[PDB]
Image (cartoon, rainbow, N blue to C red; front, side):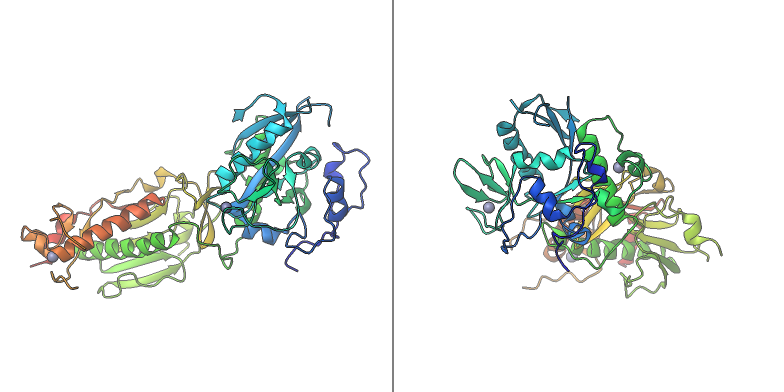
Length: 457
Ligand SMILES: [Zn+2]
Ligand SMILES: [Zn+2]
Ligand SMILES: [Zn+2]
């Protein structure tokens, strides 16, 4: 039950305006044949061009919305739209390109997909709101066959070249002209009422409709992300490592310990309200503070309202509140906050629904749109490094460190020791790693690193 059987029925009602007379009774087997492809009763890793919802969710990094609009059916030009914002016009002789024959259009498609996907996934999943022209145009830039490996590496093959008769992955596809063994899924098979725009606009106000193919491609993928990662959530699905996931996650634990420990030392809060992930552990386990946990799963739709989190019947105004990746609409003044900036560009952060983003780091977290007004009661947390550890070098070469933000006994004494200089530069790299990944740090306005110097006396 892991792959989509080709004998599964395909609802054709959405196709009958582009393809009048299409049979109501239709399987994927007959649909693929109708699209001009032949599968040959082949057991070589490619059982179906179309995939299940579950397989699509596991390969969300490969999702490319795809739409085709009749520009004027073999006799008229076609506008090819992709969720990358690209519009290509193919002739049978926000970006918008003029009409060109299929033999040059397919070269642009391979280049576009390869640059988009090489650092994201081992494949492409075309996300469709299928009405006909997009399915019948695939024969002009798609080749299928047995699963293969790249001619220059061990990755699976995603492209084919008619010039050299060879195969390549996204990384080595320069000059290739055909997409090889792509995957696809028709969102309209999921049981919607009404057209694409009416269903998309139920949940998203960020993507308009300029009535060009790329806008439909964007809305289609956006609707799919909402259905699979907003209204539905599955945190059991694991995703492969494609970047600095481990360093980013390790940096997050180190910065969280550093910031909370220093806030407790500087202001001596009697109680800390740890609001968020119900799997949370004390990040400063040796602190004397009264540590109270409050369970809140990561919100995937709208940011939590602070009124429903705190109230409905309790003294969150006592001490300090810790919101580590707990997105609320407005943080109280006595808060320590880590909030993911959905606007960040990285291979881990995919475009999301209604201004949000889909952050995929081991697991997929759809995150509500970043909002600067949520931090009005707070200020940005400045960088600093604090350590009460002994100045002792145990066991890399050294240039003396000078920094006003190395809060250690040795710097209080006027000369940073080598150990705390090593730890400072290691923490600075971790801090910059986490900030670059899109995380932002905010703190109550009274926070002052000057209060940490007298923790050495
Ligand atoms: Zn390769
Ligand atoms: Zn949208
Ligand atoms: Zn030192």
